[PDB]
Amino acid sequence: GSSGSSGYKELDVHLRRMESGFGFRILGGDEPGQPILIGAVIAMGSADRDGRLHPGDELVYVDGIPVAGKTHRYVIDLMHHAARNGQVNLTVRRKVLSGPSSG
């Protein structure tokens, strides 16, 4: 305790490379420790059809390596390995919120 009981959840996303090889894109990460939010989801593509990612989901891990504090190019180098592994795992995370005001 004294660490933070509840605030954000990570969500894992496996994607196989057998059809299009990962229907997402990756942007941000422009300085070493800028945010790495899902650049795009390829609509109808091999990630969108897995139904596990949304555009702008903040990444955490790519194929086992924590992208946090690294850059865009860092992940570009990872994807160039994951595509040989013939799948990837993409752990994203989003702060858990509730609290109405208007709707």
Image (cartoon, helix red, strand yellow):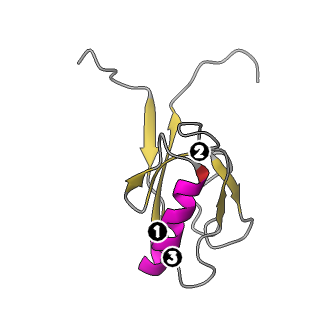
Residue 4 x, y percent position in the rendering: 34, 21
Q: Earlier in the sequence, mark 3 or mark 1?
A: 3
* Label 2 to label 3: alpha-carbon separation: 19 Å
Residue 42 painted magenta: no
Residue 85: x, y in percent?
42, 78
Quadrant housing the C terminus = top right
Q: Secondary structure at mark 1?
A: strand
Is 76 magenta? The answer is yes
Against 87, is 43 above or below? above
The residue lying at 59 percent from left, 77 percent from top is 21
What residue is pinned by disc 3?
A: 83
Secondary structure of the residue carrying tag 2 is loop
Q: Position of residue 67 (x, y in %)?
A: 47, 48
Residue type at mark 3 is Ala
Residue at screen point 33% across, 23% down: 5
Image quadrant of residue 9? top left
Q: Amino acid at mark 2?
A: Ile
According to the picture, the residue beneath numbered tag 2 turns out to be: 36
Q: How many marks?
A: 3
Disc 1 target residue: 88
N-terminal-most mark, 2 or 3:
2
Q: Secondary structure at mark 3?
A: helix
Main SS of the magenta part reads: helix
Along the viewing direction, whichever of 100 and 14 lies nearer the viewer: 14
Give the magenta part as a residue range: 73-88
Looking at the rendered image, the disc whose residue lies closer to the viewer, 3 or 1, is 3
Q: Is residue 67 left or right of residue 43?
A: left
Q: Relative to 48, is 9 on the left or the right?
A: left
